Amino acid sequence: RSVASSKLWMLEFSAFLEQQQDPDTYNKHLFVHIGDPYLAAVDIRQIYDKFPEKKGGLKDLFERGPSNAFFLVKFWADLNTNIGSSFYGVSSQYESPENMIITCSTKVCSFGKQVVEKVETEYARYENGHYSYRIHRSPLCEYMINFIHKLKHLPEKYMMNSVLENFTILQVVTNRDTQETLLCIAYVFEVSASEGAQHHIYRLVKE
Amino acid sequence: DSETDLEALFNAVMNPKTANVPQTVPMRLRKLPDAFFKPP
Ligand SMILES: *C(=O)CCCCCCCCCCCCC
């Protein structure tokens, strides 16, 4: 269990483009995918500038804790796909020992400023001695679809990475009733060059 | 101006002469883990 606090574990996360060739034929391209050991640490102060500030922002959330709920994911995104019959989606799955009502906030940021927020409420399903939470085929917001379109129309890979340096995503999963931070995941991005998508996962620490 | 201007963000890298975006410290210059820029 990599991305896991004491109360919640994210077992699956993927962003994808699904193209319908014909009514029985679907081609799915994964942009990014995640599917007990101790991870390497990153000083959170090194990335505060790339995420929303003020009350409810990353610093505020981290200081309120708990410290074990905070992670940084570095993605190498696979942009090699044919860009009517397209579905851009995000899917994720979580497990908890506790029966909770959870809220998943996803904030897309440019130069550390919030551009768009998507907020989803999830209820528990009992499964194999624990509770499961699934966000299944959540539509990617139009900003993201537009962003990917503009990225692919860039003629050089170094241009794509330059843009991505200032594009980030902040995912905050919260217990709806108690407001406890169950998971807070900061996402940073490069383009994959190896023919696909890869990731490093880090723990966010105070220093 | 606006920091969240999508067209401005892409214009900054497509046409560097007319770039109008906040200036930032490149990630590679920061105090980050050794393999942060080396894919597994
Ligand atoms: C709008 O709905 C924003 C929700 C963001 C969900 C996270 C999906 C991650 C997208 C992968 C980035 C690929 C582009 C480099």
Image (spheres, rainbow, N blue to C red):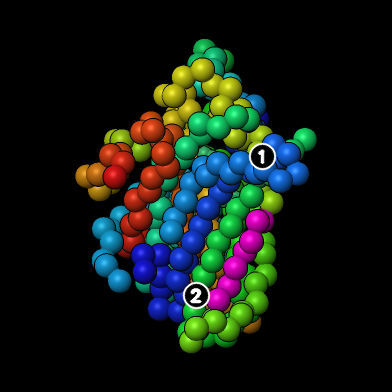
Asked if residue A136 lies in the magenta stretch, the reply is: yes
Q: Position of residue A47 (x, y in %)?
A: 40, 49
Q: How many marks?
A: 2
Q: Classify residue A82 by image quadrant.
A: top right
Instruction: Name the secondary structure under disc 1.
Output: strand
Between the residue at mark 1 and the residue at mark 2, the CA separation in whole angstroms equals: 30 Å
User: Is residue A200 in the magenta section?
Assistant: no
Of A56 and A190, the residue lying toward us: A190
User: Which residue is denoted by mark 2 in the rendering?
Assistant: A95
Residue holding disc 1? A19
**In the image, what residue occupies the spot 75% across and 44% down?**
A23
Q: Tell me if residue B12 can be seen.
A: yes
Tag 1 subunit = A
Decide whether the magenta segment is chiefly helix, strand or loop: strand
| Label 1 vs label 2, nearer the camera | 1
Where residue A7 appears, as percent x and y from the top left, is 45, 79
Cβ of mark 2 under 8 Å from ligand 1: the answer is: no
Query: What span is colored magenta in the figure?
Result: A132-138
Q: Are marks 1 and 2 on the same chain?
A: yes
Q: Residue furthest top?
A: B17
